[PDB]
Length: 595
Ligand code: HEM
Ligand SMILES: *[C@@H]1O[C@H](CO)[C@@H](O[C@@H]2O[C@H](CO)[C@@H](O)[C@H](O)[C@H]2NC(C)=O)[C@H](O)[C@H]1NC(C)=O
Ligand SMILES: *[C@@H]1O[C@H](CO)[C@@H](O)[C@H](O)[C@H]1NC(C)=O
Ligand SMILES: *[C@@H]1O[C@H](CO)[C@@H](O)[C@H](O)[C@H]1NC(C)=O
Ligand SMILES: *[C@@H]1O[C@H](CO)[C@@H](O)[C@H](O)[C@H]1NC(C)=O
Ligand SMILES: O=N[O-]
Ligand SMILES: [Ca+2]
Ligand SMILES: [Zn+2]
Image (cartoon, rainbow, N blue to C red; front, side, top):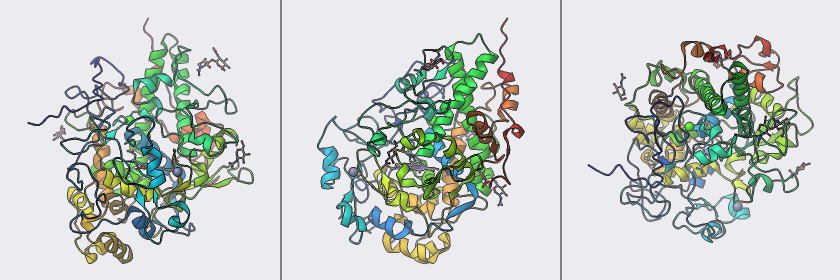
């Protein structure tokens, strides 16, 4: 009927239908449709894109173009009036560790990245957006409202660049603009291994045939490995401390250095690979490098899948888990495994779970030195604090022993992200992630709040009194109505995040539906789902049932006291046990004898 062919990246690699291992690109997962859930393709559209001109321009682009007859509010104004708060006292989640926040971010980076556009190589267009706050082409600046403190110290706007779109990088489309997913849609450790062959090979330790990943040679961690440095310049991790001059790390995912606990999580995954691979080699001395790498990569992918679906999702979705993600029934080649455009906003519920400080703790899980607790904003693109301030062990104790922020209708996003965010190319701790999220919703042509309520079979408030009942909050509903005029116009990120949480979950009804549908699809539409008969043996699944974040720590750090349930709020030493009492990963079922 139409032309579902459009594609410049058209990697169309040769599919080995006999391959026991994933491609890096995610091609060849679906036999009938080989590019399905592959990287560098369009994000899936669950609903048609909504742009000001029907094609590509965001709502808010043209000041004289209403949405449903109302001006859309400035992203930064919604952020100041609704998302911001002063008092960090009483904000912490009494039953979620900081690792619950951190694992969310890890799983997100595995599933989606819509990278900002670039046109040429060296343009004035780049700085002209920052410098002159001029809207045009892929410059879509976040303008400050009249009373904004940042107007006094930071100029007229926050620079913002439109997300890249599929087919051309620069020329527009006759159909609607579709944003790219740069990573594999499968939950497959693409953030450890990469989603492009090139990056994927640039990262491996080929030198030895042991199937190990490439490590920092310039620096080490009390025996244990560092991610290699990206020695590309200019380095944002260098720029935040020109003295220490420590570059960003080099991971499967370009975002790995964005904050120090992400860099930490990633470090442990570079590690557990090698712990697994070496264990494989001891157990299978005949196996070559490929076999150890590919088999190592496949055990790590299975680890992330299990932690995500057994430990993480049930305490996000709560009473709604069983409704959207019922027990697995095997692989369904008819399920669309693509990450949706809306999911990339839904999964940003995580921004409301980030607390204002990060701690380094000791063996007695006590403050580590005199500057043990640090403000989050000092830790963006910060690699020097890991290398020159005691490696990742003290940060990992913090992940276990400290708590996530709880989402709160009156305390949504900490000022560490809402006012002090650091972005590369940009020299300030002065960005607003909430404002960015709202601007990006529009950039991506997102349907409004009630389109999504409708999509999920939920009520669609049309008046102030309607909104008050759905949000169970008069003041929040009144502020949203003063800004948006109609609930139809509420940006999905703030609409979804404003809903009271479901019984025993950390998101409201709308997000539970959007997140739950996506997670159900990425499991059921995945030919390499760990539990799909023929991916792993009866005996391996008995032994993969064993895996744990508690054990991943024990086995790749010098930490010897851990919680059993590492995502729940754990207080030392009362809710902690010694590592010996924690089920280990019995690799005996990977034992190969072919003689
Ligand atoms: C300190 C922690 C974090 C920082 C500094 C951070 C920062 C960012 C930034 C700068 C973006 C890009 C925004 C844009 O340009 O539109 C982003 C996107 C995102 N963040 Fe966060 N974030 C954090 C934690 C989390 C957590 C905990 C989650 C989930 C549980 C999460 C999920 C996402 C998702 C899904 C996106 C969109 C990814 C895409 O491009 O497809 N983040 N984050
Ligand atoms: C790939 O792995 C090899 C073997 O594990 C690494 O070579 C070793 O490097 C360290 C320090 O550079 C030495 O302490 C070991 O004794 C070396 N062993 C051997 C057998 O060479 C090599 O550095 C790794 N390569 C990269 C680029 O990360
Ligand atoms: C830069 O790092 C050095 C250690 O290399 C540290 O002593 C110094 O305090 C750092 N400065 C800043 C501003 O972070
Ligand atoms: C496979 O997926 C499609 C679409 O979700 C569904 O209609 C079909 O019945 C599924 N097959 C099974 C056995 O569930
Ligand atoms: C804390 O969370 C866990 C799930 O991780 C749950 O089983 C437990 O009941 C919760 N504890 C409290 C005190 O609410
Ligand atoms: O995508 N990082 O939050
Ligand atoms: Ca992936
Ligand atoms: Zn700047």
